[PDB]
Length: 282
Ligand SMILES: CSc1nnc(NC(=O)c2ccco2)s1
Picture 1: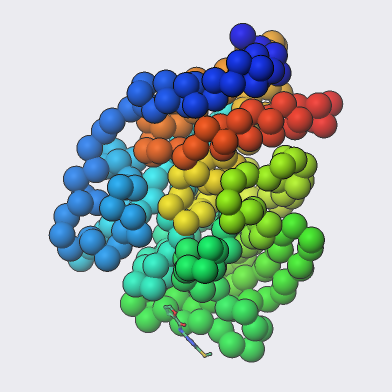
Picture 2: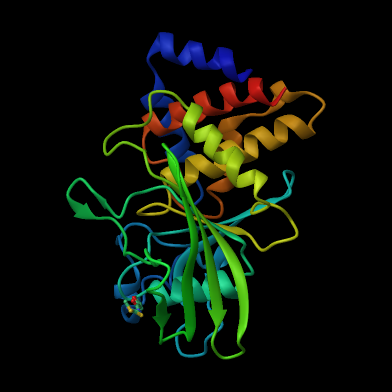
């Protein structure tokens, strides 16, 4: 079926939970043996969210190459994304090592450091120009260059320096600051505006390594972001845009990381975002 009318048909019939459970039943199951090794317990935020072995990002290290991060490679859309958990106190250096080694231009953050009165990820970037951060375990230095605070999101320019080689690179930090502590946004308008700002920066384009996207677990809000982006790109590329099947795209993405889209409300919100976004594109 088309999307917008499949949408009203699920709303009128109140069957979002049944649609979402079908997706969960059909989703791929692949091994995640490296994630479950005892030496990696303090590298995982949640025991039930792990990267598959076949698609995990490897750190360029001989001691321990593990990080909770996956490469999502979308062949028809010609887009790639790295989806990862929010960094932990003992993985902030690994996180920036990955950004460096994978040649990423942008980092997309979809959570606040504290939500619901608890910490959802480490404070992993500097908050003042004159107070830089040094990650001694991976030999990197990170400096805040500039910050632009808007009503729904903040954009930061950061300098990452590889202290071994003295090479430097400019990284863009795109921080969506207004996702509610509970539920999903009422309108997709500010989320779509944010996605378009990431696109306009070049961070999603083939001349750079894959964008790094995270929330707390790296599967819910993060899954919504890449699902919406890929579906809108396919609607631009194909002769028949009504052929784009958001459930099929989501199952393809779940071949590369488990659990993408965590609730039926996130599934409904993803439909809403793609539907509204397709009208603005034209
Ligand atoms: C204010 S001067 C300074 N503080 N901290 C530095 N290094 C780190 O904060 C760090 C490494 C891993 C997590 O935090 S340089």
